[PDB]
Amino acid sequence: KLHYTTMIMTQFPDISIQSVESLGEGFRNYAILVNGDWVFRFPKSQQGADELNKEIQLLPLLVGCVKVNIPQYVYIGKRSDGNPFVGYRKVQGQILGEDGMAVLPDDAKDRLALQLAEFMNELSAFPVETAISAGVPVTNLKNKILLLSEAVEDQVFPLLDESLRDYLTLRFQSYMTHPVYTRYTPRLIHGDLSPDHFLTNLNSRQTPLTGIIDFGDAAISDPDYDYVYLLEDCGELFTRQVMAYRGEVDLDTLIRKVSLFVTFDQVSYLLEGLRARDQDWISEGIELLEEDKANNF
Ligand SMILES: NC[C@H]1O[C@H](O[C@H]2[C@H](O)[C@@H](O[C@H]3O[C@H](CO)[C@@H](O)[C@H](N)[C@H]3O)[C@H](N)C[C@@H]2N)[C@H](O)[C@@H](O)[C@@H]1O
Ligand SMILES: Nc1nc2c(ncn2[C@@H]2O[C@H](COP(=O)(O)OP(=O)(O)O)[C@@H](O)[C@H]2O)c(=O)[nH]1
Ligand SMILES: [Cl-]
Ligand SMILES: [Cl-]
Ligand SMILES: [Mg+2]
Ligand SMILES: [Mg+2]
């Protein structure tokens, strides 16, 4: 508390702090709300610092290209050399969350699907070279999944029933051996496009999506990756609606491709629990892998 407030007030003489409250946190950042108005967002690691340095350069170039609100860093602070933090006016609205889309009526879901399709479209139109110049990495997704499959063999396979191992090997091979999945034209992607990052004003019937946050995973990569959490967290029906508005073709094949990404996400989630040495997380991740197999076959 006093730790974050002292850094803020030392570095920003125009901020007089009357209230401070925790707002949210993810794997890479801790966010607090100052005076009900300002989000101060603090990286949790050097990797978080790298991602924030990317966002500092990228987001100002994106503001004028998207039709939702995104964070605009007004305050740029430093913890010490190479350790930035930022402050931005809260992106307004209600975070939708996972449990949000499940309850929404048809007209609202239709409008949200249209707005998300448009947002993805805008990212796919953004000049890749400008993004790279802003520190956005070029992530060859085929090579990333190859490295993942090696890690799984080493760290994950020992924990599994051989039948679940057989399933995972099948999923990795189904992705890796099909050019229909592995070849793509790279684009700027958000990289973590899950509904915990969707800000809404459901009072607006026709334009319920108002904001998107957390661009820390932004990459030049496969645009189909930005469907992964739509499928995992919003469901196949909604995901297919977004795909239709975007003019995707052969949705059965595309859904299969994204479902492979979902499998790999479940592996990744377990690997994070193994890295953290969290037995509850490990057990949860093993269960999610079993559910992935049961849901697909
Ligand atoms: N909370 C419970 C859920 O947690 C995971 O899903 C969440 C991901 O963890 C998030 O992403 C983060 O973790 C990823 C690796 O897993 C990273 O690549 C990414 N950069 C991180 O921001 C993503 N934004 C939302 C998604 N619902 C499990 O998969 C899911 O089964 C489980 O129900
Ligand atoms: N309502 C609201 N919540 C925010 C805002 N910025 C961050 N948050 C919350 O803080 C959490 C952590 O921020 P995020 O950038 O996603 O951190 P990361 O996932 O660790 O990279 C988010 O998931 C939100 O819950 C904002 O502008 N408005
Ligand atoms: Cl992956
Ligand atoms: Cl398969
Ligand atoms: Mg986040
Ligand atoms: Mg992030």
Image (spheres, grey):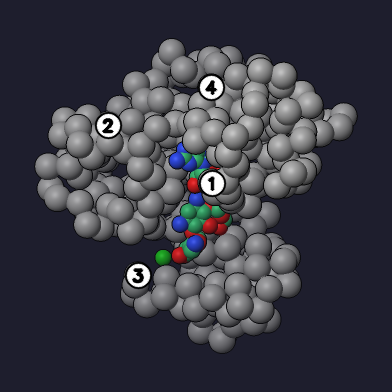
Q: Give the Cα separation between the discs numbered 3 and 1.
A: 36 Å
Q: Give the Cα separation between the discs numbered 1 and 2.
A: 25 Å
Asked whether the viewer can see residue 22, the reply is: yes
- Kind of residue at disc 3: Asn
Q: Nearer the viewer, mark 2 or mark 3?
A: 2
Q: Are marks 2 and 4 in contact (CB under 8 Å)?
A: no
Say which label, 2 or 4, has the lower sequence index: 4
Q: Are marks 4 and 1 in contact (CB under 8 Å)?
A: no
User: Residue at point 33% right, 31% down?
Assistant: 210
Asked whether, in this view, residue 126 is left or right of residue 160, the answer is: left
Disc 2 target residue: 115
* SS at badge 2: helix
Say which label, 2 or 3, has the lower sequence index: 2
- Kind of residue at disc 1: Leu
Beta carbon at label 1 within 8 Å of ligand 2: yes
Say which label, 4 or 1, has the lower sequence index: 1
Q: Position of residue 38 (x, y in %)?
A: 55, 30
Disc 1 target residue: 23
Q: Is residue 181 above or below residue 293?
A: above
Q: Is residue 58 above or below residue 213?
A: above
- Kind of residue at disc 2: Gln
Image quarter in which the C terminus is found: bottom left
Q: Which of 204/240 is in front?
A: 204
Beta carbon at label 3 within 8 Å of ligand 4: yes
* SS at badge 3: helix
* SS at badge 4: loop
Asked whether the viewer can see residue 190, the reply is: no
Residue 123 image-quadrant placement: top left
- Kind of residue at disc 4: Gln
Q: Nearer the viewer, mark 3 or mark 4?
A: 4
The circle on residue 296 is 3
Disc 4 target residue: 72
